[PDB]
Image 1 (cartoon, rainbow, N blue to C red):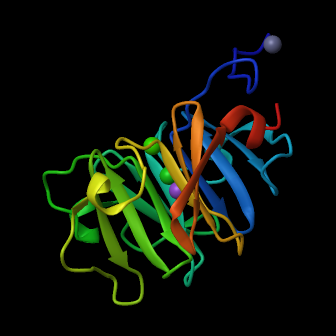
Image 2: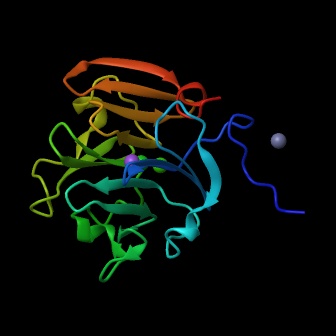
Length: 200
Ligand SMILES: [Ca+2]
Ligand SMILES: [Cl-]
Ligand code: NA
Ligand SMILES: [Zn+2]
């Protein structure tokens, strides 16, 4: 007798964060992860996030992999953790203020590094920030409003990821994802997370 764990396809799971880390896609839900190497193939899981990142709290809010450093950055509450493989770095968790976020944002929604410009975007409610990974600082003139800067992208995102050299960013909210053409921000298509990411 084991405890009940979430069942993809049989339940409507809205993930906390999604990230491609070291060529693998991770879907995070509470203490668990499912992973796959290519999107429409049914992911292995649930594994426990603790067998890879033991220091992470029981729920993350957003995850991305900083491309250059190939470090995984996880947000949970008003802290973030940066790892190289399963090794937590020097002095993490740090408050979100060490990333350049204002002390008023107490949690973020979704985060990704966008291959279109290799800048990191951090989404929180109706706003986002663009973080410079080489200068290790936020770019000026942020936060901007998602409604003002993105095309057909909803506020309160769940997760965002840009896979590989695929040239699409994927915004996940509720049961659907929006697929953005990185070369044509005008062209946004929608699809179903269960059918297209979880291979249900
Ligand atoms: Ca989230
Ligand atoms: Cl995310
Ligand atoms: Na992400
Ligand atoms: Zn079942």
